[PDB]
Amino acid sequence: GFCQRPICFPN
Amino acid sequence: IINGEDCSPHSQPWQAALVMENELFCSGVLVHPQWVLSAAHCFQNSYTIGLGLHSLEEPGSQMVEASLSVRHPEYNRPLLANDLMLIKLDESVSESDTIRSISIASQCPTAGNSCLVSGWGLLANGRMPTVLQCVNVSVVSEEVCSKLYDPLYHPSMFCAGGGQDQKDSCNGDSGGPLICNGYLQGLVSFGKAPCGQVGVPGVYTNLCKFTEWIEKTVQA
């Protein structure tokens, strides 16, 4: 997944 | 900052620390005497902003209040995109030897551009540093960024890093500067979790797309 460095996108 | 080193003291004099109750949650970048750029996901109702710092724990350093900020009107539309805001300091700071604004790049990023990212976010060892960290990263092409960050790549973003050297931004670095060829090119925005994976660049706010919005806001 992706995360702001916060919202994460699971992918 | 993953796999960087202590910055040379005051070599990044535009670096701003965003702290709440004296705890850092983001950085920003001084772009004019009264104006700090940061990531829109760092938005708060008010800010204490550390300028001229090297350690968070120094002649010329200042702690200033900022009571006003504005997120880009399309932040998070689509998700993660347009990740910038402007913070207006409650007083202008007279440029000094250790507090200085940086210009935004007039060119947009292209693969191979050489950059430096700095911040007080997580280290490779999982700890939070006291001293500002710096590391070198290089821009990769839009096609690399799009493929790696499918399905959410948007032209308000660009990618830098991703080497086998595992140099990257990480949590707590958001809003801080990516300086490419000596100009402010990006803000730390997001990346894959974990940070510092082999081959995996971080994602930065593509400031060359926002210079008109930034300066219209400054001048309003």
Image (cartoon, coloured by chain):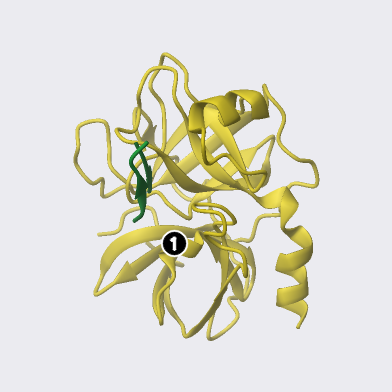
Chain colours: A green, B yellow
Which residue does the image show at 59% across and 56% down from the upper left? B82
Task: Residue B131: give x, y in percent of width and height.
Answer: 31, 47
At horizontal 62% and vertical 70% (from top left) the residue drawn is: B73
Q: Is residue B35 visible?
A: yes
Chain letter of the residue carrying label 1: B
Q: Is residue B158 left or right of residue B65?
A: right
Element on which disc 1 rests: helix
Front in this rendered view, residue A4 or B146: B146
- The residue to which callout 1 is attached is B41
Q: Nearer the viewer, residue B218 or B158?
A: B158
> x, y (%) of residue B8?
45, 40
Rendering coords of residue B166 (x, y %): 38, 21
Observer-nearest of B213 and B62: B213
Quarter of the figure with residue B182? top right
Q: Amino acid at mark 1?
A: His
Residue at 74% in and 66% down: B213
Residue B90 position (above or below residue B197):
below
Classify residue B18 as left or right of residue B103: left
